[PDB]
Image (cartoon, rainbow, N blue to C red; front, top):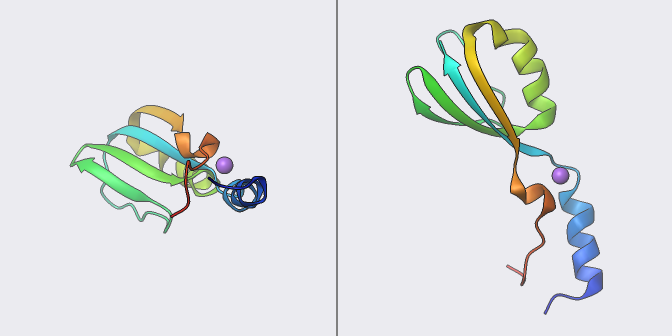
Length: 85
Ligand code: NA
């Protein structure tokens, strides 16, 4: 299906990004989220899909209003497509 050339081009393009997924409990009032953030959840518990490079300074800034945290690297960091799209 995909050629070796197409695969390494894909890896070259994709590897720049480091999507992660963060589970949080806490208070989310008075927070502005970076552009890479896609925030799901309820008033006092979130799941955030975001870029690692944005997560780091965000946590340093706002981490005092979070009470529990779990961080996962998104599986797309190690995915190659089976076909093009
Ligand atoms: Na990556």
